[PDB]
Image: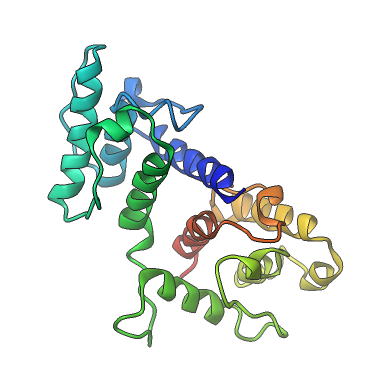
Length: 230
């Protein structure tokens, strides 16, 4: 299901950032997203690295120290005009999945997805509508591949390869692309983007070759491409 994939994707995204913390003790790794954010420490760390700001933190063990640290993170975001539609400290401290996923998505949008500007876009297209237009424009010439959406259109790997073939034309062979299975095409795309473009592998080939790829995870990964070659 799309939610286990989303947890998955979100977890790697958060970890990529955690380990670049400037402070050693904060350089942590999450195993389960629905446990390892509860105490608020990694949420605060994640906001520290993404913003470069130094945030207060509460050291102890206690239940209400978890709450305090979540509140510091939520308060940070609210002070930056992020609409936390309604989340309490509790939701995160208790490990609620929907809201924990929602909070991470909100952070991904705010910090990563929302700077997407492309030339000749419309005024009130969304930031996802703007990414889409970029993706389309990135493959305008390749022979009858559409990008219509951030799900089914990505399933066979063609889009990703075609995108990477725009400055590593040398590293991928689009011909083999139209001969390869979905899985081969995904692995390759994702392994090329890591080695030669500096793009962390957020998705597994298995997560994407399914009838309905999870829209947020695909957007997270494709945003990451955009960041490497706009």
